Image (spheres, rainbow, N blue to C red):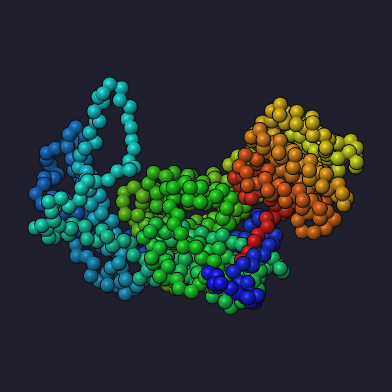
Amino acid sequence: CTSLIRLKKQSIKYPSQNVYSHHWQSKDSPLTLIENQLIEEKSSESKINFEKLLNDKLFNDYLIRLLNQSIKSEFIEFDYKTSTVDTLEIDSNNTKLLEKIQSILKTIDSLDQSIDLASLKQVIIEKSSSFKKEINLIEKSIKRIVSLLKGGESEHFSPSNPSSPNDTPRYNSNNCSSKSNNTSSGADDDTNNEETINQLNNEPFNFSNSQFISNQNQLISKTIVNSFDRLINSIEIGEKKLIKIIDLSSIYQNNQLSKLLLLQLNQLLINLSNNNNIEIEYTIPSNTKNIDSIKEETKSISNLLNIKYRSFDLQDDLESNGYLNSNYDLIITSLLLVSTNSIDSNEVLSKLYKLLLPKGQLILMEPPKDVLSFNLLFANDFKQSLEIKSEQEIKSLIRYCGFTKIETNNITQDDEEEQQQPPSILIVQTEKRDIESMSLTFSSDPESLNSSYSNCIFIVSKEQKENPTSYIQEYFDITEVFCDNTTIIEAGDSELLTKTIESGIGKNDIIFFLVSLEELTIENYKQVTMQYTLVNQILLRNNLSTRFALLTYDSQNGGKNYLGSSLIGTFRYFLEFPSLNTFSIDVDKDSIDNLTLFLRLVDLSTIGDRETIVRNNKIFVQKIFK
């Protein structure tokens, strides 16, 4: 009699793929910023020489030459400059191009028409590292400017035909494709030299070869890894910590920043492979054009740092792509304000802010607008390059989206006998609004915590401090119960409880359970657990949107009340349902008075999961580690 399964006879295969542990780390980020008073570190020599490159009329003559050749490259025989015609688009001519060219030539005339780009060009090329791969960028700027303004446009902002009468404009640009490709060898035979107009167009702004961008990345990497060094040196005994780091410069700048980031992170952890009370979920998203470079540049770094090679595009919904509100701790972003056309910078900052954990660092390395030629190296069109703003505007926009402690880190180098310069790139590392104080809205205003709730019912026990006023005040005052109907219903009084919760309770109605704060006997805990289960059953059976927050004591790390875990377990069972919005908080005796904080804990937006521990006013979540 033969079976069909290989039989492993009582073997001992030491489980390595199935062990998951449980800890409790403080959800509010323990990450701490660096003091801006020490940001002096020299690695770049090309930025000082670039600021020296200004006020050099020979570069201006190079500008004149490029503008002349761009004027010539438009059309071989087309009129300009007095006359025919002086009109403008639209109705009807390409004279918008004519006026743009005349303004460009008006700027051209002053002031030099002499020899250019031999001596100073050789000197600067040998001085910084090479400026041929900078003149190429500045030339390709105007070359692709004329390529874009040529594009498919020289006309055709024409009025859409209003017929039929009262035809509202309807736009929809998805689910469209061309039919059909390569019919009768169309545009295939007799083809050659048809793509010479745009040949530097497919070669992007190169930053890897030159070492100045690498110096920028080195400064950023060292400043981040020093804070991480501080954190790991302040590691706690027997408490693993999960860190969610996402870098969005991996789609905008070269990966080199993240390259050195991973290199030094893994190097540091390898030098310090003696404690495993910390793990790092480092993640690198890309737009399906740098995933290849990212995954091929990194080979074996995932030893202790869980790496997730994914895709994040800032034009899609955060929740749709899987990213959640108050989900990830640290975000590092460079070349961001130069990377948008239609998205408001406040909207980009809101995108960054929503994902952030409480006080989670937002590192934003953005260019200032003190030198325009310095901004011409970050975008290739008249639109994105000027989407950048000044330092004060960046600060105000960061404070606009609810950020505290803006840290201005002006990258400062110091080359001897070489002039000073404005900051090479402004680095602002701010933190999310402190989890101690928010409101349910996006920006802090206590309208949602005060006089926003209509009915707040309190489950109490009349076996200690029979009066409910002092029973609640025994742990936190009753005055902070801010609702139009301060109601208290006896524990076990489920009939009037059913009547009250079935007559109607609004979305801003909450029910705190203060019976799980006393030391439960060896029999009564089943009784109160049954009461709770019936309460949640009646809540769900009518599909209500009531907010519930259970408050328990010492029932999630062991102590005087180890019996509330039954309540917590059945509550956990209910959480799989979407109709029942319920939370649970375990607090000690010495931090039990934070009623306003508990009201804040109803936040699905700025706070994360629906189970937390408050110790010494610090909010914790349980983390499970492979």
Left or right side of 304 for 525? right
Q: Nearer the viewer, residue 145 or 40?
A: 145
User: At 25% across and 30% down in the image, what residue appears?
Assistant: 160
Residue extending farthest top: 165
User: At 51% across and 59% down in the image, what residue appears?
Assistant: 246
Q: Nearer the viewer, residue 93 or 509?
A: 509
- In percent of width and height, residue 542 lies at 66, 33
Residue 425 is at least partly visible in this image: no
User: At 90% across and 37% down in the image, what residue appears?
Assistant: 466
Q: Quadrant of residue 171?
A: top left
Residue extending farthest bottom: 271
Q: Quadrant of residue 48?
A: bottom left
- In percent of width and height, residue 182 lies at 17, 52
- In percent of width and height, residue 113 lies at 19, 59
* Figure disc tally: 0
User: At 86% across and 36% down in the image, what residue appears?
Assistant: 468
Q: Quadrant of the N terminus?
A: bottom right
Q: Quadrant of the C terminus?
A: bottom right
Q: Nearer the viewer, residue 244 or 8?
A: 8
Q: Quadrant of residue 232?
A: bottom right
**543 above or below 53?**
above
- In percent of width and height, residue 167 lies at 30, 25
Residue 127 is at least partly visible in this image: yes
